[PDB]
Length: 184
Length: 15
Ligand SMILES: C[As](C)(=O)[O-]
Image 1 (cartoon, chains in turn red, yellow):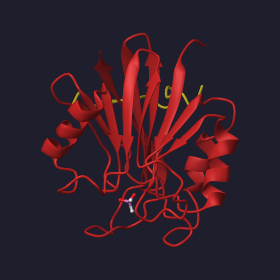
Image 2 (spheres, helix red, strand yellow; image 1 turned 135 degrees about the horizontal axis):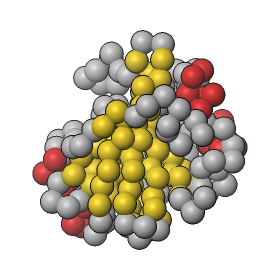
Image 3 (tube, chains in turn red, cyan; image 1 turned 120 degrees about the horizontal axis):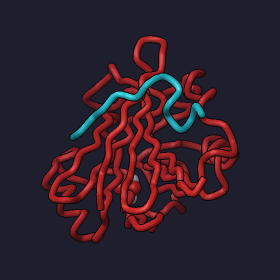
């Protein structure tokens, strides 16, 4: 082994917008493979937290603007391997998903990787030796500004000073997988 | 940024 597998996901909006994750996603996410879970928020209820605890015994969640649990922290900074990682739902970032506001957050937090959600749009890019991840929405839940949403989630394989970011997407009725490498 | 596709069954969740 020796790799740290980190699941990244959020904006499920269960059950108000969606009842479950895609069946094909549930087949991939099985106990005993993932070390840590970093959740951007908007679960939105304890049942989804409970489900995440069956997948890994180290679960991190930040508070979304539709989360029921107001005890979640607003943002969180964690260290996995050599990487310092920052986590924010993103509805605080003004305007929605502006690259300038996110870069501001990165310097404020002093992280190698900045994870955020709220736009329900997967992105993963490198900007000034800094890495930015949006997992999208793992259920394909609509939001304001967008209704035709591709369900997705991110898997980070952290080893030494490389992060290998897998992106999983339900396109049509099948899972498509891409990978992006980021160096520290 | 450098988005390479990944062959069937080569992602961590499948072997
Ligand atoms: C609804 As809030 C305090 O997480 O921006």
